[PDB]
Image 1 (cartoon, chains in turn brown, blue, cyan, green):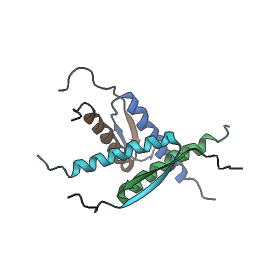
Image 2 (image 1 turned 60 degrees about the horizontal axis):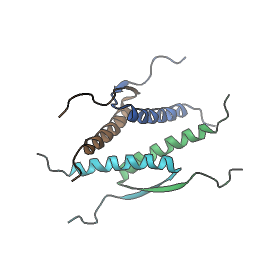
Image 3 (image 1 turned 135 degrees about the vertical axis):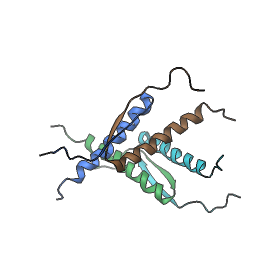
Image 4 (image 1 turned 180 degrees about the vertical axis):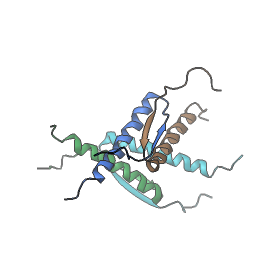
Length: 42
Length: 42
Length: 42
Length: 42
């Protein structure tokens, strides 16, 4: 549960708060799939 | 001319370099439309 | 059980097979969140 | 002139009208870059 090296770590400047929330949504979307990857297929 | 009065300015931490390049592409996509918004009609 | 009362149903023509696979990935991303929405809290 | 030799042609069923408008926006985004690809440099 959480330990050695995680994935790399970059950043991105998003101008405008409106579109900002839009990108954040896609961010959690991809990160969610990653959590389903190391999960037993069952 | 130009003026520092741009929209707000936020940021986002994108883990993984692979997924990073993916988000960056979408960023330039929306920003491109913004440049076409201030384009005088014809 | 299930019931055909799903949300609306539209479509989108994606030219290019390369870009096609890219959009399809985002589709499953949002749909995944929907499945977590009806997940009873705990 | 033009020629019907465009890229492949696939499709995608997007449930929900709300999320539909979201994907459509990304579609025009990538297509815009394609139009800038065949733009003679200067």
